[PDB]
Image (cartoon, rainbow, N blue to C red):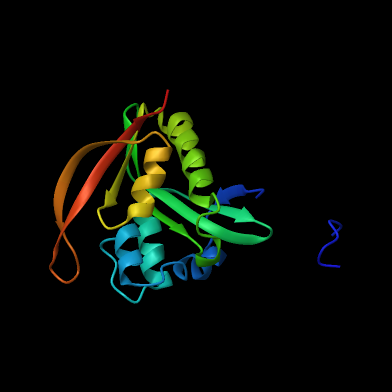
Length: 166
């Protein structure tokens, strides 16, 4: 019966080749792809994703109920100093459910433990309100704004944020 009472655990691991196709399916439009991978060209592809992974560090997936739901890496890393989070991507069926929050916490721990980072940097494009609000909730503070140019040659504002790791 619908009216009887009677009838978000996440894990993580390094990204693997088999995860590529799934992750590359996460950006749903040119805007989404630009926010998470500004040098990528639409349509996104596994080869573009793999090129990013090869050039970056710490590529990690978040898994729930047997599905890869999130992905992130570092695009800058400086031992004893900071890491900068990149390619933060969430499956479209799992938006707003705590997957990015979870994976950011995992990446903060990785930065602390592996890189002895004192600071995490995250930069977010101005149009991505969801991102700005999430990072704010997680204790990131805005430090600067930089002018960047989108694939149409339009001028956007990159909000550069950071958080101490402890």
